[PDB]
Amino acid sequence: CVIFPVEIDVSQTIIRDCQVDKQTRELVYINKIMNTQLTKPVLMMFNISGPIRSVTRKNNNLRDRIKSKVDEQFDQLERDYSDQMDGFHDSIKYFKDEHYSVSCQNGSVLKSKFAKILKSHDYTDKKSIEAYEKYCLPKLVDERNDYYVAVCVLKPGFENGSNQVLSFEYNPIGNKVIVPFAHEINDTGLYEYDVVAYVDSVQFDGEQFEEFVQSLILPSSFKNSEKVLYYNEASKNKSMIYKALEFTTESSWGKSEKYNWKIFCNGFIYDKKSKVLYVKLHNVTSALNKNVILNTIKA
Amino acid sequence: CVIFPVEIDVSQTIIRDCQVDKQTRELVYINKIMNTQLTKPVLMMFNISGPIRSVTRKNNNLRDRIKSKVDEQFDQLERDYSDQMDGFHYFKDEHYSVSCQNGSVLKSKFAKILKSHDYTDKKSIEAYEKYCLPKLVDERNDYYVAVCVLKPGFENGSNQVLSFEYNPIGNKVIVPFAHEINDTGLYEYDVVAYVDSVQFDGEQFEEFVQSLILPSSFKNSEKVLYYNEASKNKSMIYKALEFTTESSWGKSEKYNWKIFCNGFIYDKKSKVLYVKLHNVTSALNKNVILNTIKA
Image (cartoon, rainbow over all chains, first blue to last red; front, side, top):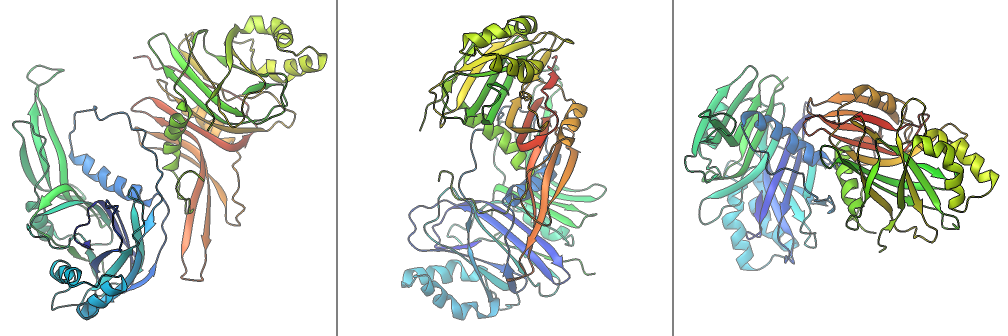
């Protein structure tokens, strides 16, 4: 998530983190990188709540199943009265998934090991090393280094249109899980997000979710009267904290019987019964650049 | 489907049957002839729900778009852990000659049709009337018959294609899966079809899927599971081959595979039927017959 070199353009990040057993959890992390030049590797790093133990291999369809599952929780919040975008389109699966090379650093040793790490990847100039320490290191360590760091390397020859993927099991320190939403720092202070996540065996944190959702800026539909609404709702077994873009259009089938659109819902949907968290931050921007940190279920 | 000489070999059948207007439908039928040593023409025939009105032509490689649409629906049902590289590891499409005949006329003039294409001997003729004709004429309906001729010297690396518009009689659509009869009583299928504007027939699908024998992965843990699930905007009736592999070498990691998904996927919203019967065998040798949507 904290990506280096800092130029690098990414989108469509998909994440899944599930309890494997009482002391193991698995992180599946998928994204799509846009650069073609790149002669050196992409070093993507991010915080996790415990040491990595082994990498896993998932089936070729997991990616779309994660995304489909997240989307079907949010669709339920929307009211999209348009069937235009229609006719699925002739794009075909063709590019094979690329795999990041994974290693792990205890948060406590990263500051003393980072330059060594860049060097093993042929990044030796002062320019690159200072960029990393200025824009990346800070999103990976804080004087209270109790969390770990996943170091993901992407060899440079990868094919543009590929999904870059990785998955591994780790051992959470103290019933914590870190969903790696944070990005490397940038000069403007505004960050763009485009990610969905599925995380199970987790406790609800209404306040952390409110803070994240209130900070979100949604995409505009460019209609005259659009308004952004903020929701902090609870149904039978779900808690929903999100924003939605809403507006009105006159009835084509009735007279003054208007249509109340409710689209681009982004936020957090928590299933109180399954203990599952669904997150969607699709094309939204925010000044908050942080991970979501939760407590796992205890027994 | 109903191919003569009864001894020819075919694979990769791609079917697309769509409503063109209120009274008209178009059938696109693609396959591949394997035999390379042919002198006397391939005669493929099958029932359609009404008379053909125009034989048509499509852009080259329409074949790939139809197959990708059906593949996309079934691929979603799978859990494959394979390492398949990036796509590729020539030939324009060849074309069948198409004409039409009703039940009645074929039953008595089939002999003639045969001779007309070099099939003069009593051997060929009795074989057609024994293996082919019974899959084409039924005394309980009228049904017309598409007559497709593939001329010798065609390319095998090419696809053999045909397409035409026809006027369905009685609001019906016949999806041409049935093959010529053979003595083993088992039928191998290798076809995908996209059929729009049709009503769901849950029972006809269940029966056809239950009869399927799936290909194997030669695994000790493989089993065939039957699925009849919904999305209540999507209905999936199919069989899948499931198995587990593991290699406690690295770490005790287990992969749960679910592949070779074959059957019927009906989109209850768009009224579209996706059918996949790829390398499956069955005792049933029958077309699928449905009702067109009446808007």
